[PDB]
Length: 246
Ligand SMILES: C[C@]12CCC(=O)C[C@H]1CC[C@@H]1[C@@H]2CC[C@]2(C)[C@@H](O)CC[C@@H]12
Image (cartoon, helix red, strand yellow):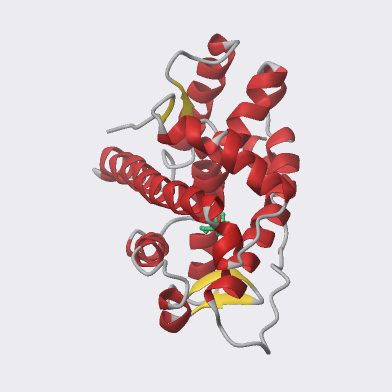
């Protein structure tokens, strides 16, 4: 039942709306990634809200959790698309925004792109299952909270704990075995922790970009600028931190 829902609520394809006839320029490429961010967020909000047990969380916590976790959530799914599609050779941000080494450079994001490409690579190196992925992605929504807890921190802990048990559940079967089960869970929880440093590098990047957006001609859509100037700082100043397994 858990998996039927995750499989059922999983978002479809989201295009960034990039003009691929115009030259790659920092401004263009980043305005596109931002718009894509605005579009994908609309879908993350719907998905999250349709997550089993999600409604147990307090209304403000529901929103807060989405607002702190979107970067890692989008980065993780983006790595999956790059994987199932381009076998991790390039970053499949959208069907109309697939970065090559040249785009990775002309974006002043080469490094972060290397790390995300590296993540996508892990889905391969580890042979991640579509279902392990659905579960791992679900748990990333419950992977970053304020240091002083949320309004109803007891519902989040319940919720989060349950998602950890489903992850172990979907490996403890044919998706693990012999001496795998223990090793399999150590590597998946290790792969999950890996998305966090990558998310933080992008948080600082996007934040700096937003402060000087008017000068590099890159513009951030409504929700992006608001969430980047209201929520992301709380993360960057240490008020909200990721939950690490290791
Ligand atoms: C979440 C997004 C948008 C959705 C996606 O597939 C990947 C991804 C990772 C890079 C983010 C991007 C949104 C726009 C950001 C935050 C830029 O300002 C700098 C890094 C970009």
